Image 1 (spheres, each protein chain N blue to C red):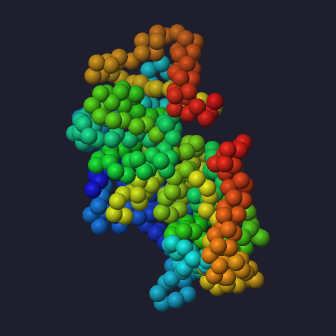
Image 2 (image 1 turned 180 degrees about the vertical axis):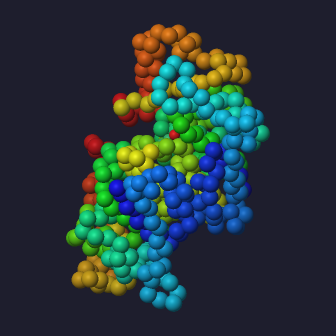
Image 3 (image 1 turned 120 degrees about the vertical axis):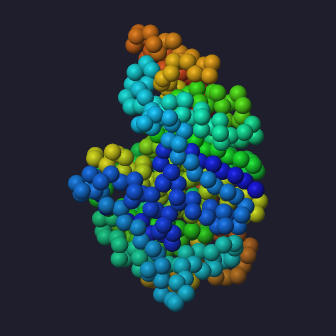
Length: 213
Length: 212
Ligand SMILES: COC(=O)c1cc2cc(CO)sc2[nH]1
C-alpha cells in the first residue's frame, strides 16, 4: 500500500495518472493531486516573486509551500522535488522508492522553488531533489508523471540493452524474422539475443559497458 | 511551424499536451499537435495490437501489420519518426534543439515489450527514424516519454513559449529561522556572480560529478 500526493499550480496536467490507472483500480496505490493555490490567502493568489540578487524570471515563495507541506506531510514522508539541479533518478532509485508508504511530489514552475522550503522540510522528514535527465523542461509536472510510472510498476502487487523483438507473420513486406528465432533451439536463441544486445549496447550506450561517450 | 502527430493505444494520456498549448501560438499557426488511437488501424473485430514473441519469452510484441498501416497513412518522406524506447540512443538537450526546427514529428508510442523491429527498419528506408531513451529507468510504455519530448522540443520553438544551477531565494528575507544569504542583498554584483559560481561548483561536485 502506497500513498502519493502531488502538489502543483497545474493540477489538470496530472490527469494522465488516470498503468498507474490500473494500479489505483486494484486498490494498491492511491494518488491525489492538490492545487498549490489552495494555500494562498491574498486576492490574487500569488505564489511567486522576483529573485534576491537579481536574474531573469521568478521564484516560488516559501510561505505558500510551507503551509501546503505542513498539512500534507508527516515525519515518515519521503519528499520528492523534481529539479534540473537534482541527483539523478535511476532504476535503482525507482526500486528504492517502491517500498515507501508515502511519497509527496512538489512540482515547481518559473525558475524554481525558494531553497529554504527543502531546507526546512529536511529538519522534519527525508528530502530528495532529483533530475530525470539532461534536457530542459518548463516545470516539474512531466517529471512527476515519469517518476510515478517508474515507481508504481515495481510495487509488490503490480545493465545491458534489450535487443530487437519480432512477432507474426514470419515474412512481412519482404523482410524475414531471423531464422534462428523460428528454430526452437533455446541455446542458439539465447546466444543470438546476447550478441544482438551486445551490438546494440556498444552502438547506442557505450557508457553502460565502460567506454567513452 | 511544426506539426506533431502522436500514435498510442492510450490517446487520453496525451490530453494535457493539447491543453498546454497557448491559444496565440495555435491561432498564429505556429504549432499543431494531433493524437491518434492506434486501434483505428487494426484488422480484426477484436482490435488486436499485440501477439506472442518469436523465440519465446515474457510479455507481448506489437504487431507489424497494424503499425505499418498507421505510419503509411500519417508519415511522408519529410517526417522525422521518433520511437521512445529504453533501448534507444539518449535524448539530450542537443537532441531537443535539433528537432525544434523540424516541420513534422511523428511519435510512435509502444507498450508491452516493444514494436516488431521490422516496422522501424522498413520506415528507415524512406524517412529519418530515431529510437531514443529519456533516461536510465524503465517505464511500461512510451506515453510519458512522449510528453517529456514534446515539452522539451516545443519550448524551444520561437513563439510557443556544464554546471548545475545553485539555490534561489525570494521574499521574505527571513523565514522559519532561515535568512537569505546576505551577499545577495549587498548590491555588489560582481561579488554576487562569484558567490553563485562557487555555489554551482560545489553543487555539481556533490550531485553530478559525471559533469566534471
Ligand atoms: C521548477 O521545476 C522545473 O522547472 C523543472 C525542470 C526540470 C527538468 C527535469 C529533467 O530532469 S526535472 C525538472 N523540474
